[PDB]
Every structure is written in structure tokens, then in C-alpha cells.
Image 1 (cartoon, rainbow, N blue to C red):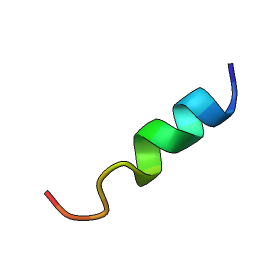
Image 2 (tube, helix red, strand yellow; image 1 turned 30 degrees about the vertical axis):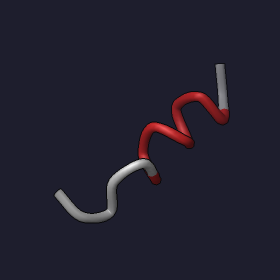
Image 3 (cartoon, rainbow, N blue to C red; image 1 turned 90 degrees about the vertical axis):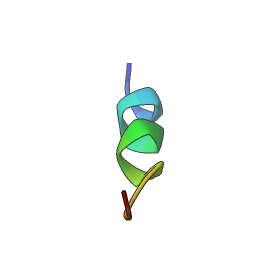
Image 4 (cartoon, rainbow, N blue to C red; image 1 turned 180 degrees about the vertical axis):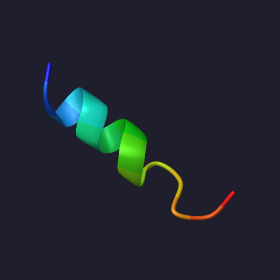
Length: 15
């Protein structure tokens, strides 16, 4: 609902 969409954004930074 929040960090879930935040953790999914930071879970990359390089792909």
C-alpha cells in the first residue's frame, strides 16, 4: 500500500 510500491522500485536500480 506504500513501501510495497517503494521496495519494488528500489529493488533494482540496475537491470
